[PDB]
């Protein structure tokens, strides 16, 4: 059984030209509020591999909601942010991911697509008014299909992370490789963003974004814990500067705790 889009890559389709960002189906199984900024597809679900999957498909140039030539297309769900900075504060997302395709431009720095991200505002200015903290970006790995064609067969997952609050661009962010996953392989995902007691320090605090991907932990401390005011997560599909991205999410859960 299959839920993969295989037709030509186009910018918009009727079935995906939603009138508002909050266009959703009745009773979605994925948790969180829909934020649909792509006219290629809408959120929908499929029943396969013994699970119910939310379907996040976006294509290059399909953002009919943001002002043109600004932000990339996306279909995401946003989760209530943890608006506290005490140790023990966290946002915790869990789910099962399938990757079927990501964007590709032929150059690493503009290739790949995000399936989740950690974000949170900070004091003191710097960057955009709703700044990213780090995003989890999947890049294509090609191989043969069995008939002499190069196609996406696996995906290198990298973390695009801030060097400093609100950082963007070559100077503002660094890319860290995490691990490879196979096309259509079911991957357990956990992402927890939060504040904890700093051991190397007293009564100071660390702001972290710790992921578990297919059983392996990738932990990371956010720069300048003291400037951050909240922890937030979004997931789905975001960024496709060439071609198409297709993410599948099953059994999503979200918890948070706010501790001062
Ligand atoms: C800032 C956004 O943050 C998140 O939301 C998300 O990761 C997003 O990624 S995205 O979905 O792929 O878009 C981030 O968006 C990128 O933000 C960059 C930014 O800092 O605003 C954008 O880069 C800026 O603009 C670039 C054009 C510039 O790159 C130089 O400029 C030109 C050009 O005008 O011809 C081309 C080349 O990009 C490069 O020569 C960036 O400069 S830098 O060299 O990287 O430091 C930067 O000014 C980026 O386009 C957004 O996608
Ligand atoms: Ca849509």
Image (tube, grey):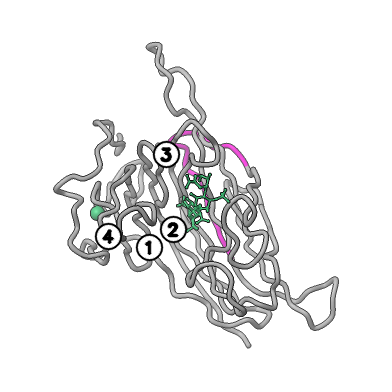
SS class, disc 3: loop
Which quadrant of the figure has residue 258? Answer: bottom right
Q: Earlier in the sequence, mark 2 or mark 1?
A: 1
x, y percentage for residue 221? Answer: 70, 63
> How many C-alpha atoms fall within 10 Å of the one at disc 1: few (<14), some, or many (≥20)?
many
SS class, disc 2: strand
The disc label shown at residue 103, or none: 3
User: Where 22 falls versus 184 (above or below)?
Assistant: below
SS class, disc 4: loop
The disc label shown at residue 65, or none: 4
State which quarter of the image contains the N terminus: top left
Q: Spatial distance from mark 2 to mark 1, Cα to Cα?
A: 6 Å
Q: Earlier in the sequence, mark 3 or mark 1?
A: 1
Seen as rendered, the residue at the extreme bottom is 260
Q: Earlier in the sequence, mark 4 or mark 2?
A: 4
Q: Spatial distance from mark 3 to mark 1, Cα to Cα?
A: 20 Å
x, y percentage for residue 198? Answer: 78, 74
Between circles 3 and 2, the one closer to the viewer is 3
Q: Are marks 3 and 4 in contact (CB under 8 Å)?
A: no
x, y percentage for residue 111? Answer: 48, 39
Q: Spatial distance from mark 3 to mark 4, Cα to Cα?
A: 20 Å
What's the magenta region? 179-192
* Nearer to me, 21 or 92: 21
Q: Is residue 95 left or right of residue 7?
A: right
Q: Spatial distance from mark 1 to mark 4, Cα to Cα?
A: 15 Å
Q: Is residue 79 left or right of residue 66?
A: right
Q: Is residue 141 left or right of residue 54?
A: right
- Residue under numbered circle 2: 235
Between circles 3 and 4, the one closer to the viewer is 4
- Residue under numbered circle 1: 77
């Amino acid at each position: 059984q299959t839920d993969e889009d295989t037709g030509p890559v186009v910018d918009c389709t009727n079935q995906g030209t939603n009138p508002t960002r909050d266009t959703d189906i009745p009773n979605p199984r994925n948790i969180g509020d829909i934020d649909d900024r792509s006219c290629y597809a809408n959120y929908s679900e499929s029943s396969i591999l013994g699970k119910f999957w939310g379907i996040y498909n976006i294509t290059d140039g399909s953002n009919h909601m943001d002002a043109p030539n600004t932000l990339q297309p996306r279909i995401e769900r946003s989760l209530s942010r943890s608006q506290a900075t005490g140790a023990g504060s966290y946002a915790r997302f869990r789910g099962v991911l399938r990757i079927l395709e990501v964007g590709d431009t032929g150059t690493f720095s503009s290739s790949g697509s995000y399936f989740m991200q950690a974000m949170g505002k900070h004091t003191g200015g710097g960057g955009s008014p709703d700044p990213a903290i780090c995003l989890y970006r999947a890049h294509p790995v090609y191989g043969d299909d069995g008939n002499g064609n190069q196609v996406q067969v696996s995906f290198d997952i990298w973390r695009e992370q801030i060097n400093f609050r609100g950082g963007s661009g070559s100077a503002g962010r660094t890319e860290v490789f995490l691990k490879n996953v196979l096309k259509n392989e079911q991957i357990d995902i956990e992402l927890e963003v939060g504040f904890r007691d700093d051991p190397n320090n007293p009564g100071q605090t660390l702001h972290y974004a710790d992921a578990k991907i297919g059983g392996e932990e990738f932990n990371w401390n956010i720069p300048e814990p003291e400037r951050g005011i909240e922890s937030g997560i979004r997931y789905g599909a975001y960024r496709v500067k060439g071609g198409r991205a297709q993410f599948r999410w099953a059994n999503t859960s979200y918890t948070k705790d706010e501790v001062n």
